Image (cartoon, rainbow over all chains, first blue to last red; front, side):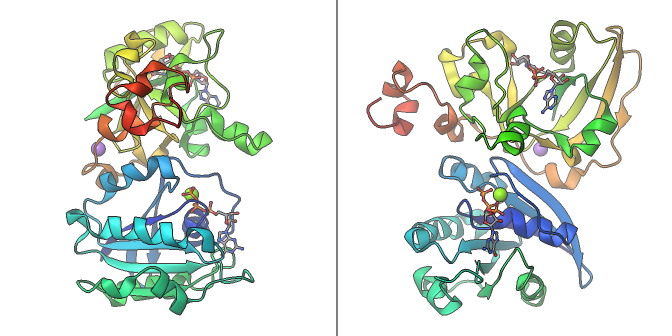
Length: 162
Length: 185
Ligand SMILES: NC(=O)c1ccc[n+]([C@@H]2O[C@H](COP(=O)([O-])OP(=O)(O)OC[C@H]3O[C@@H](n4cnc5c(N)ncnc54)[C@H](O)[C@@H]3O)[C@@H](O)[C@H]2O)c1
Ligand SMILES: Nc1nc2c(ncn2[C@@H]2O[C@H](COP(=O)(O)OP(=O)(O)OP(=O)(O)O)[C@@H](O)[C@H]2O)c(=O)[nH]1
Ligand SMILES: [Mg+2]
Ligand code: NA
């Protein structure tokens, strides 16, 4: 079985770190992503084709040109970044309201739980307005991408829930 | 459909670089410099006319014949070079469509990849020796068609915001760039 995954979120959320922690088992130093990275990862007998697309403001209009064929959305949020949680909400709802994304289940990585000021999953769920999403499954998974905690639990949710 | 990039680096070096990466990427890891993703700067290049060290784009051609002509210009001093055959994906932009009539060197006929081109996107390559394509295409075993077969280059409408004309440039007061104008332009 195969699953085409689109991983989106604002810049600095932790997307590329997640991708390379999963594919390499290691924590890498990153460059801000302006195009995309793509890797295939095998877990509990599922081949996950994960697309890591750049989240800076100027290149968000390109997100939709990756929606085709997507079976799960991974939306990564920087939980220490309270100043941008609301912008994160607006970008999420713009994604899920595109017709090409109607049937993609949504995993939220509530990332950077290691940081002191960090918003926890209850708070993230509410600041993202997720209960207004009533037409598909979603779930908020706490994570620290650098240490890898939360990631395979997220991947487990994706398999179980599709 | 496919794109074609003439490049003097051999396939083994490309594989170990993870693909065809922009110059700006090395600059970033080497001295923290942020990549320049203004398409106009990429197309204009440096005052003196050369490729910027911070360039966030990688140039490709739309035909094998154009890529070869580029190789016989830019790469004339290399007795061996490669033409990489590349699938389409949405980090690619038709420079002349995005810059429109303001494209500074429209003869380049460039389709450029923002952030570079991963190895999995490279279908294969032609070796060019003393300017001649004598050999059949060598297929990239690392290519992944299913990744790319359903994706296209970005449409120009979603490229306009990346045109990056300088702030006082008149394009910013006209369609289509006016909808992305920085403040005061
Ligand atoms: N290369 C092409 O097939 C191509 C296609 C269409 C248009 N053009 C035009 O040709 C002109 C020059 O383009 P170009 O893309 O060859 O210049 P470039 O600087 O990217 O490439 C020139 C050479 O520099 C080296 N190089 C490139 N990127 C590198 C990297 N990241 N790390 C180490 N070495 C690297 C390679 O030896 C390469 O052949 C531009 O005007 C462009 O519009 C080129
Ligand atoms: N403290 C902490 N830092 C993290 C965590 N995950 C990622 N980071 C860091 O946050 C910064 C951004 O990480 P990236 O993986 O590049 O984020 P990005 O979402 O890919 O950004 P774009 O490519 O611009 O879209 C880096 O310094 C990472 O090391 C985490 O769980 N905890
Ligand atoms: Mg990234
Ligand atoms: Na394609």
